[PDB]
Image (cartoon, coloured by chain):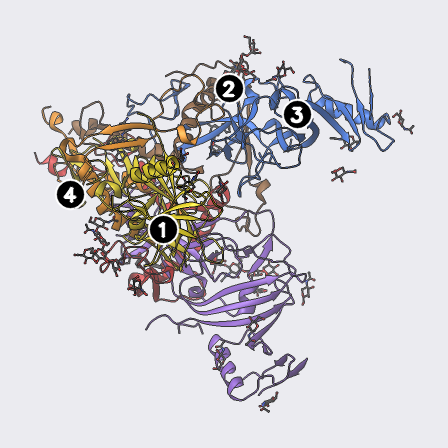
Chain colours: A purple, B yellow, C blue, D orange, E brown, F red
Amino acid sequence: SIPLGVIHNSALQVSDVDKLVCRDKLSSTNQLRSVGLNLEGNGVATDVPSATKRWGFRSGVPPKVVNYEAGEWAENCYNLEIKKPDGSECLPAAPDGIRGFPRCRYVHKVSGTGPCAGDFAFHKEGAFFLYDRLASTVIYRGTTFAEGVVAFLILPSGYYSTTIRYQATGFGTNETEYLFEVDNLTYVQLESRFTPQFLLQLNETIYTSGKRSNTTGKLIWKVNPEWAFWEXXXXXXX
Amino acid sequence: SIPLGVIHNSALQVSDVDKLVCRDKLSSTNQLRSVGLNLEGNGVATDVPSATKRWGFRSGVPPKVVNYEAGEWAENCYNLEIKKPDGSECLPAAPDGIRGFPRCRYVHKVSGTGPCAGDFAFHKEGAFFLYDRLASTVIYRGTTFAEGVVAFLILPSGYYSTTIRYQATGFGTNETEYLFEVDNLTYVQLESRFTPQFLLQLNETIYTSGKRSNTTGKLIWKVNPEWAFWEXXXXXXX
Amino acid sequence: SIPLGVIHNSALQVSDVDKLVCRDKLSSTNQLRSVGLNLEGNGVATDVPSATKRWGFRSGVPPKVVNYEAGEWAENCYNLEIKKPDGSECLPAAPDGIRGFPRCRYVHKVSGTGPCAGDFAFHKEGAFFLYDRLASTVIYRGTTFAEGVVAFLILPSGYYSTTIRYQATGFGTNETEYLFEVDNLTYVQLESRFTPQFLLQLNETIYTSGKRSNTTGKLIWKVNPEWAFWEXXXXXXX
Amino acid sequence: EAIVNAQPKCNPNLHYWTTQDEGAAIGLAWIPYFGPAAEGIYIEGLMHNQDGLICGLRQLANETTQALQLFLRATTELRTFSILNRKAIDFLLQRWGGTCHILGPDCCIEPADWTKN
Amino acid sequence: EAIVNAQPKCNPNLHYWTTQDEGAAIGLAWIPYFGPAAEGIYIEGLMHNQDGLICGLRQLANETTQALQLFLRATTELRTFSILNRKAIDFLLQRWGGTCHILGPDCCIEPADWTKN
Amino acid sequence: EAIVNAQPKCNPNLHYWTTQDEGAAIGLAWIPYFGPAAEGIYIEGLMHNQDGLICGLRQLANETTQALQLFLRATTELRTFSILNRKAIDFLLQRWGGTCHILGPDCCIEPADWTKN
Ligand SMILES: *[C@@H]1O[C@H](CO)[C@@H](O[C@@H]2O[C@H](CO)[C@@H](O[C@@H]3O[C@H](CO[C@H]4O[C@H](CO)[C@@H](O)[C@H](O)[C@@H]4O)[C@@H](O)[C@H](O[C@H]4O[C@H](CO)[C@@H](O)[C@H](O)[C@@H]4O)[C@@H]3O)[C@H](O)[C@H]2NC(C)=O)[C@H](O)[C@H]1NC(C)=O
Ligand SMILES: *[C@@H]1O[C@H](CO)[C@@H](O[C@@H]2O[C@H](CO)[C@@H](O[C@@H]3O[C@H](CO[C@H]4O[C@H](CO)[C@@H](O)[C@H](O)[C@@H]4O)[C@@H](O)[C@H](O[C@H]4O[C@H](CO)[C@@H](O)[C@H](O)[C@@H]4O)[C@@H]3O)[C@H](O)[C@H]2NC(C)=O)[C@H](O)[C@H]1NC(C)=O
Ligand SMILES: *[C@@H]1O[C@H](CO)[C@@H](O[C@@H]2O[C@H](CO)[C@@H](O[C@@H]3O[C@H](CO[C@H]4O[C@H](CO)[C@@H](O)[C@H](O)[C@@H]4O)[C@@H](O)[C@H](O[C@H]4O[C@H](CO)[C@@H](O)[C@H](O)[C@@H]4O)[C@@H]3O)[C@H](O)[C@H]2NC(C)=O)[C@H](O)[C@H]1NC(C)=O
Ligand SMILES: C[C@]12C[C@@H]3C[C@](C(=O)N[C@H]4CC[C@H](N)CC4)(C1)C[C@@](c1ccccc1)(C3)C2
Ligand SMILES: C[C@]12C[C@@H]3C[C@](C(=O)N[C@H]4CC[C@H](N)CC4)(C1)C[C@@](c1ccccc1)(C3)C2
Ligand SMILES: C[C@]12C[C@@H]3C[C@](C(=O)N[C@H]4CC[C@H](N)CC4)(C1)C[C@@](c1ccccc1)(C3)C2
Ligand SMILES: *[C@@H]1O[C@H](CO)[C@@H](O)[C@H](O)[C@H]1NC(C)=O
Ligand SMILES: *[C@@H]1O[C@H](CO)[C@@H](O)[C@H](O)[C@H]1NC(C)=O
Ligand SMILES: *[C@@H]1O[C@H](CO)[C@@H](O)[C@H](O)[C@H]1NC(C)=O
Ligand SMILES: *[C@@H]1O[C@H](CO)[C@@H](O)[C@H](O)[C@H]1NC(C)=O
Ligand SMILES: *[C@@H]1O[C@H](CO)[C@@H](O)[C@H](O)[C@H]1NC(C)=O
Ligand SMILES: *[C@@H]1O[C@H](CO)[C@@H](O)[C@H](O)[C@H]1NC(C)=O
Ligand SMILES: *[C@@H]1O[C@H](CO)[C@@H](O)[C@H](O)[C@H]1NC(C)=O
Ligand SMILES: *[C@@H]1O[C@H](CO)[C@@H](O)[C@H](O)[C@H]1NC(C)=O
Ligand SMILES: *[C@@H]1O[C@H](CO)[C@@H](O)[C@H](O)[C@H]1NC(C)=O
Ligand SMILES: *[C@@H]1O[C@H](CO)[C@@H](O)[C@H](O)[C@H]1NC(C)=O
Ligand SMILES: *[C@@H]1O[C@H](CO)[C@@H](O)[C@H](O)[C@H]1NC(C)=O
Ligand SMILES: *[C@@H]1O[C@H](CO)[C@@H](O)[C@H](O)[C@H]1NC(C)=O
C-alpha cells in the first residue's frame, strides 16, 4: 500500500498494515492530508546547471498527475521554454487547470534549444514536478514548478518573487551551455557556483557600471571566482 | 462542512456535525441525493434585463463545475451569444459533456455585443448556472441554463419549449439596450415589464396585423403601458 | 444495483442485496476487481463481415467510458479507418489516455468507406469496445479494440501480434464488400468462412506463387471453397 | 441548525426532473444504440409542500451555496462528482472511526436484546 | 441469484493480462523515466475452470451489462472510475449504516467469546 | 516501520502554503465573482521540528515516491484525486469489513463500561 504517515509516541512513522491499531482514530476525511515537500529541503543542488541534469526526455510513458493539498514555500522554481533547433516545441502546453507553483522566491526561466529526444521530460530520480496543488511526472511548457515528492498522513514578510532568465544550448545533454541574461544583448557565462543572490547583485552592478552592450550585438561576460539556502564579443571581470 | 439536509420531526433541517444521531440511518449511497433549485422559485425577477444584471465578467478566477442528480422544471432559461464589438467571442464554448438545461418553458436566447471586461462571466450573487445535471460557476456560449443553487440531503401535459430571441448592445453594463425580435427586420423595444406570454402574444399580433417591416431596413416598435409565474424606422403602438 | 460477483459454496454467484451475509469479508478495496471478458469466449463469429454487422452508427447518445483493471488475451481485435465517400472521417480520434487493447493475436485493420449515418458507432447488442483498461460504448478511429463486457466481483510463449488489412465499401450497411489485402495492388474477395490463419497462409502462397499484380492496376482474386478458435482485373483460384 | 425560509417568495410545488434508478427497460431500450437520446432519459414528478419540505429545500440550497463555493475554490478538480461519496465516508467515520465504547454516546451499538440474555 | 451460463460456447480457460500490485521493482524500474513503456506494464496469468468460475465469469459479465449501461446513461461523468469504491462504501453502509442491534440479523457483531465471560 | 531521515540535509523549518477549511468570508468574499484570484486563495503557516516531525515528513515523502509512482503507472486516470478517500475506505474495511468478534484483536469494540453492568 502507498505509505500513510501517523504520529505514534511523539514520532512520525509509517502505519504498518497487517497490524491494526484500534487506538488510532479517523473521525473524518478532513484528518487525511496529502502533502508536497521540495527536494530543496533535502539539500539537493538548486542551481540551473545541476537541476536540469536531473530531467530527461523519454517516449512511450504516458504522463500521470496526482493532486496534493498543501505545499512548501520554495526558494528555487523553474520555468522552461525549450525548442528543437528547427523551432518546434519540446514541451507540451499546460493542461487546463495546471497553474504554476504558488510560492517561489526565484523563478529560473530557461529558454533555449536542445535535441529533446523524447515525447515528454521526466525526473531522472523519480521525483515529481510540483505545480499548483497538482503533481505531474512530466514538465509542461512555460509553467513554473518546484521539484518535490508527495506524502500522505493522518492528523491527530509577504511574498516576493523575482524572475532570473537564462539562455541554453544543448539542453538535456552532457554539453549544455547556459547564459545568465541581464538584458536582450548582454549575457554572463553561467557557473554552478552562482547563487540566485549573486546573479541579482551581478546584474545590478552591470547596470550601474554601464557594462551593458552599447552596440547592436551580443555581449558575453566571463567572471573570476570572486551550506544550504536556509542556513560576437566576449570578455572578463574580476 | 458543506451542509447536508435531513428530515427530523416532520421538518427538514441541516444535520449538526458535532452532535451524532445514532437513530439516523444511511443504508446505501442511493439515500444521498444532490439537488438543484431554480432562483425562479424564490421570486427573483426573470425578465431578461433584470436577469442579465446579475451576471458579470471577471478574470483570474478559474471556472468550477459540480454535478447534481435532480432538477426542477424551469419557466425561464437563458442562452447567450455575446461578442465584443470587434466580433471576438465573449463566452467559451461548452466543454465536452455539458448540455443545456433539460426543462425550460421559455428559452431567452440573447445575441448581441458588450465590452466583456473579463475572461469568464460569473453570477454576481454567487448562484450557479444550472446545465444538464452539471452546475457551473460560469456561463458557456450558446448553452441553455437556469439560475440555481445546489442542495445535498439524505432521503429517509408534456414538455413544450419555445425560444424568445433578443438583441443586445452594451451587454453587461449599466446602459444595456434590448430588442425583442419578431423577425430578422422587425424588433420591439424591450421593457422589464414584458412577460414571456406578452412577448409571444405581441409577436403574433404583429404577424397578423401585417405590422412587420415590408422594406429592407430594420423596423423598431415601441409600445404603450398596456405576482410570481406560478401564482432606420422607429414607431409606436397603443 | 450493478451486479457484484462473489464465490459462495465453491460457485460464483451474484450477491443478493436485501440479504446481508455477515460471513462475507471485505478487508480492503484491493479485494474488489473490475474485469473484462471478450465476446470471443462466448462463441460469437469473429470474422470481419460478421463482427462489423454488430456495430452501427447513431446520434443523440453521448459516449460513455468505464475502466476495468484486468482483461483477457484476445484472438481477434479490430482497428477501423472509415471515411465517408467525400473523405470526411466517420470515427472520432481516440481521446487522450485511450490506447489500443493490449493483447491481440490478430488485429483486423479495416479501411474503407460507408455512409456513416450517425455521430458515433455503438455496439448493436449493447456490448463494450474494450481498450487498454478502458471500456467505451463507442468506436474510436484507428484504435485497436476487442468486443467485450465488464464484470465486478469480490475476491475471497510470448506475445505475437500480426495485422490483417482489409478494404471496405458500404461499411455499416446490408451490402458491404470486403477485400483482404496482400499488397497495395493485390486483393482477395473476402468470405465469412476465411479464418485468420487461412488469410495468412493464402497471403504467403500468393507471394511465393508470384500471383501478385505485376502491373500498375488492382488485381482481385476469388477463391474456391477449399468449432471455436480455442478448440481492373478479377480472377479465380482452386 | 434549523432552516428558516427567508426568501422573498416560495414556489410551494416542485415539478422535478431526474433519471430513473435502474429499472428493466422494455426489451432493448437499455442498449445505447437503440435507447433514448440525451433529451429523453428523464422522468418527471411533482411534489407538494407536505411538512414544508419544498420551501425548506429552497432555503437549504440557498444556504449551502457559501460552503459549496468555498469548497470549489479550494479544489483543483475541474468537475467534482465526489461530494456525496465523501459524505457517506464521513458518516461512517463519525460512528466507526475509532473504538466503539458500548453505552457511550458516540457508539451506536445497542445490546438491548443482548442485555436480556 | 445464481449464475447459469446460457452462452452458445464457453472458453473454459482464461489467459489474462493485468497490472501488478506494487512489487519492488528491480532497482530503478519504478522511475517513469527508466521504467517500461505503456506496452510493457502488464503481467499475465492462466486460470482454468476449477469450480466452474471461468464460465460463470463470462455469464456474469454478460448479465452485468444492462445495469452497467443504465448506470452509464444516467451519469454525466465522461469516464467512470468510482464503481468499486462506491461498492465498498455500500458494503459498509449495509452493515454499519445504522445502530447495530446485537443478536439481530442485520448486525454483524458476534459476542461469542464475550458471552463466555 | 520507522522513518529514519537518510537525506544529505534537512530544512528543519517548514514554511507552508495551503487553503483554508471553509471559514466565513468577510461579507461577499465567497462569491467567485468578487472573491480572490487564483493567486490569493492561499494561507501560510510556519512549523518547526518539534518531535522531529519536519525531518520525518521529508523522509516520508521521499519513501512514498516508489509506491506512488507504481500506483500512477497502473491507473488510467489522467489525474488522481481519490487516494485519500480510498485510504479512508480502507481504514473502515480493516476494522469493520467482517464480523466483529468482541475481545478479539481485530475488533475495536470495548464493552468496558458495558462489562460493569
Ligand atoms: C530519496 O532520497 C534518496 C537519498 O537522498 C535519493 O537517492 C538518490 O538517488 C539518485 C538516483 O536515483 C542518486 O543519483 C545517482 O548518484 C550516483 C552517485 O552519485 C555521485 O557519487 C559517486 C561517488 O560515490 C560519484 O562517483 C558519482 O559520479 C556521482 O557524482 C551516480 O553514480 C548515478 O549516476 C547516474 O546518473 C548519471 C548522470 O545522469 C549517469 O551518467 C549515470 O549513467 C547514472 O545513470 C546517479 O546520479 C543520488 O546520488 C541519490 N542520493 C543520495 C544522497 O544517495 C532518491 O533519489 C530520493 N527519491 C526521490 C524520488 O526523490
Ligand atoms: C440566498 O438568499 C438571499 C435572500 O433571498 C439572497 O440575498 C440577496 O443577496 C444579494 C447580494 O448577494 C442582494 O443584492 C443586493 O441588494 C442590495 C439592496 O437591494 C435593493 O434594495 C435597496 C433598498 O433597501 C435599494 O436601495 C437597492 O438599490 C436595491 O434596489 C443592493 O444594495 C446591492 O447592490 C449591489 O449590486 C448593485 C447592482 O449590481 C451595484 O450597483 C452595487 O454597487 C452593489 O454591488 C445588491 O444588488 C439581494 O438584495 C439579496 N436578496 C434579498 C431578498 O435579501 C442571496 O443572494 C441568495 N444566495 C444565492 C447564492 O442565491
Ligand atoms: C448476453 O448473452 C446473450 C446470449 O448469448 C446475448 O443475446 C443475443 O442478443 C442479440 C440481440 O441483443 C441477438 O441478436 C438477435 O438475433 C435474432 C435471432 O438470431 C438468429 O436466429 C433466428 C432463428 O431463430 C434467425 O431467424 C435470425 O434471422 C438470426 O439469424 C435476430 O432476429 C435479431 O435481429 C436483429 O438484428 C438484425 C441484424 O442487425 C436486424 O436485421 C433485425 O431487424 C433485428 O434488429 C438479432 O440479430 C442474439 O441472437 C442473442 N444471442 C443468443 C445466443 O441468444 C446478449 O447480446 C449478450 N449481451 C451482451 C451485452 O453481450
Ligand atoms: C501535519 C501538517 C502540519 C502543518 C499543517 C498541515 C495542515 O494541513 N493543517 C491544517 C490544520 C491546521 C492549520 N489550520 C492548517 C490546515 C498538517 C499541513 C502541514 C504541511 C503543509 C505543507 C507541506 C508539508 C506539511 C503543516 C503538515
Ligand atoms: C427529497 C426528494 C423528493 C423528490 C424525489 C427526490 C428523488 O430523487 N427521489 C428518488 C426516489 C423517489 C422517486 N422514484 C424519484 C427518485 C428526493 C428528488 C427531489 C427533488 C428533485 C429535484 C429538485 C428538488 C428536489 C424530489 C427531492
Ligand atoms: C477472480 C480473478 C482470478 C484471476 C486473477 C484476478 C486478479 O486480478 N488477481 C489478482 C491477485 C492474483 C494475481 N496476483 C493477479 C492479481 C482475479 C483477475 C482474474 C481475471 C482477469 C482478467 C479477466 C477475467 C478475470 C483472473 C479474475
Ligand atoms: C557527453 O559529453 C562528455 C563530455 O562532454 C563525453 O565524455 C561523453 O562521451 C558524451 N556522451 C556521449 C554519449 O557522447
Ligand atoms: C527582449 O526580447 C523579447 C523577446 O525577444 C521581447 O519580448 C522584449 O520586448 C525585449 N525587450 C527589450 C527591452 O528589447
Ligand atoms: C537588473 O538590474 C536592472 C537595474 O534596475 C533591473 O531593472 C532589472 O530588473 C534587473 N534584472 C533582474 C533579473 O532583476
Ligand atoms: C559602453 O560600453 C563599454 C564597454 O562595453 C562600457 O565600459 C561603457 O561604460 C559603456 N557606456 C558608455 C561608454 O557610455
Ligand atoms: C452607469 O450608468 C449610469 C446611468 O446610465 C450612470 O449614472 C453611471 O455613472 C454609469 N457608471 C459608470 C461607471 O460610468
Ligand atoms: C435570419 O438571420 C439569421 C442569421 O442572420 C439566418 O440564419 C436566418 O436564416 C434568417 N432568417 C430569415 C427568415 O431570413
Ligand atoms: C411569431 O409569430 C409567427 C406567426 O405564426 C410564428 O411563426 C413565430 O414562430 C412567432 N415567434 C415566436 C418567437 O414564437
Ligand atoms: C406594410 O407596412 C405597413 C407599416 O409598416 C403595415 O401597416 C402594412 O400592413 C404592411 N403591409 C401591407 C401594406 O401590405
Ligand atoms: C439491405 O440489403 C438487402 C439485400 O442486400 C435488401 O433486401 C434490403 O432491402 C436492404 N435494406 C434496405 C433498407 O434497403
Ligand atoms: C501502400 O499504401 C500506403 C498508403 O497508400 C502507403 O503508406 C505504403 O507506403 C504503401 N506501400 C507500398 C509498398 O507501396
Ligand atoms: C504476406 O507475405 C509476405 C511474404 O513474406 C509478408 O512479407 C507479408 O508480411 C505477409 N502479409 C501479412 C499480412 O502477414
Ligand atoms: C506475373 O503475373 C502473373 C499473373 O498475374 C503470374 O502468374 C506471374 O507469376 C507473375 N510473375 C512473372 C510472370 O514473373
The span from disc 4 to disc 3 (Cα, nearest Å) is 63 Å
A30 displayed left or right of B116? left
Give above or below for B15 relative to C166: below
| Chain name for mark 2 | E
Quadrant (top left/top right/bottom left/bottom right) for the C terminus of chain B:
top left
Where's residue B39, x and y in %?
A: 26, 43
The span from disc 3 to disc 1 (Cα, nearest Å) is 51 Å
Q: Residue at x 19, y 30 (%)?
A: D48
Front disc: 2 or 4: 4
Where's residue C157, x and y in %?
A: 65, 31
C68 displayed left or right of B131? right
Give above or below for B36 relative to D19: below
The span from disc 2 to disc 1 (Cα, nearest Å) is 73 Å
Give above or below for D74 relative to C155: below
Say which residue label 2 marks. E49
Ligand 5 falls in quadrant: top left
Beta carbon of the mark 2 residue lies under 8 A of ligand 6: no
The reply to whether dot 3 and dot 1 touch (C-beta < 8 Å) is no
D11 displayed left or right of A137? left
The span from disc 3 to disc 2 (Cα, nearest Å) is 42 Å
Q: Which mark is residue D3?
A: 4
Q: Residue at x 30, y 37 (%)?
A: B197
Are dots 3 and 2 on a single chain? no
Front disc: 1 or 4: 1
Residue B164 in sight from this viewpoint: yes
Are dots 3 and 1 on a single chain? no
Say which residue label 3 marks. C170
Are dots 2 and 4 on a single chain? no
Q: Secondary structure at mark 2?
A: loop
